[PDB]
Length: 212
Length: 232
Image (cartoon, rainbow over all chains, first blue to last red; front, side):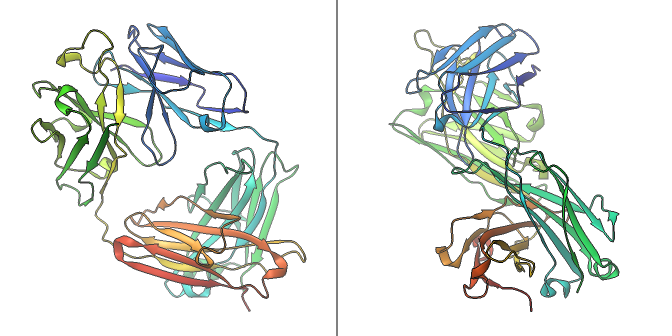
């Protein structure tokens, strides 16, 4: 099988920028390399076929180059509708294989998250389970670290995170971390705290509550 | 203008079977070779199968060999994917895609994929799981009593333990949209999904403005409205 490696995996850029992304094949594929665009919740669109030929209807600011193992996609003058994920795909032999994708996101100024912690509702506790939620609201860049501590004891393996797509109006991200405990475990401890590390924060911020 | 539409996706138990169909309008499908691909939640694109315009050539990814069968009916202007011995990891959006024709000289059936896929359908979702259809429980994420005076407060709803996807969430029956973040669902170890929806509002409004999240889970015909208020 032919492995396709795209670089970078994520790219921050502004409207009007010239962006190039690379696609390396693990073996020669001649010029049979295609590029696709995909946005959340919609099917991919063919942009370039056979390495450098523009698909009809695709804006001329897209161009492709390469043959063999080294290929590049260039977007001249990035436009708002170009922020999306891009995949390369070799089409010289089966299995047809794709790169891991390159996500082009909107660059903006660093923004620290607003942090909120939510205790479990009394209603949920009747079911034998407690969910504790930590919200990181409207921050940039995407990278952030959230750690749970119960009575100052670091929690591991009992939380799940979710992150929104980049916001269309302010280009920020938001993130939730949910700590799941048994009712018995929850009622055994007093202090529940969420500690957040982010580039926009000079020092980690902690939000906490006391059970009851 | 051409159209390509997949159908047949649904919920299946592990080991079950399912048949997907791909129907087109505006052109003769038999003039084109065809492929099936899939995209698991939050993951990349995976090629699955290929069939030549005549139907004489077929190729398969190792991941589905011996379990899936691609076919087509040129009179019915359709392409099909028969799936058997389905596994949880087969959960994905399944795409039917037409292979692009050559600009001058045509690619024979045995290598008909050389020029990429120029028309895709919007996909059909296949979910393989042992979980049973179940509506969500909705719990309040109550605004903190420490909310800054004259500042910004956060509140939300936890939508827990439903199956299958999707659920939709609104706030105040659509009157509250600014500042809302409805997170993508996470699949829990129980096989059930959970998500939270949050919104930031003026702290001064917590005493006067009622906040309600409206949750709809069509697979179980469940609608839930949960008032989120400061805890006494």
